[PDB]
Length: 214
Ligand SMILES: Nc1ncnc2c1ncn2[C@@H]1O[C@H](COP(=O)(O)OP(=O)(O)O)[C@@H](O)[C@H]1O
Ligand SMILES: [Mg+2]
Image 1 (cartoon, rainbow, N blue to C red):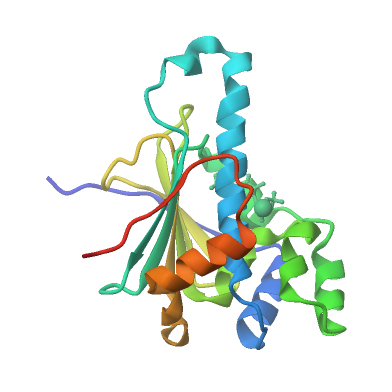
Image 2 (cartoon, rainbow, N blue to C red):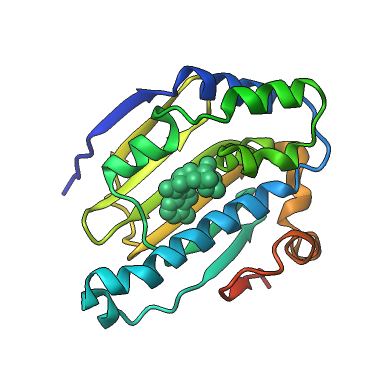
């Protein structure tokens, strides 16, 4: 039986839209930091679960390990970062992923104009959009205990959609899927991934596993 999904489209906040064109339309060295940003966001989500214990012991009764999986698919040209963190409600995606102003956006854009390293992006409050250094389209699937499963997705161009995901259930947590641009396939190689997690993500307080296709 055919399933029905409601799809809502939203504008990026003006400055975030602008930071996004800048990220996509300019060359930057050191684009590898995108993974560091996605891992540290997964790692934060995992911390939330740890402390969510204290606000209601209920969350103690979960079986899932707290961890991060990296999954390259060369057939598809995707890189997926999966965590079992706290996930996000519909409201959270809309508010946290593109609609609401961050104070550091304009500062970041001026800094890059004066030639700062793209690596500074996390300290300006806008770490998430580093994904657009390597990917031409990002999908975020997420499931929070308070809510149903939602997919967020953007190819930039000024807006994003949120819909109910009636696909594969994922359980609590967040999956970030990057459709890599054609020039950026190095980041599907096992050795390159291990190199950059070694260099930039060495003090994450949770297990990271990399799945490699035999
Ligand atoms: N894997 C994730 N799990 C839960 N929430 C996430 C995840 N990735 C991003 N977010 C949400 O998106 C927001 C934006 O993240 P980011 O752009 O890196 O800024 P910051 O991490 O400094 O808040 C986060 O504050 C978080 O609420
Ligand atoms: Mg962040």
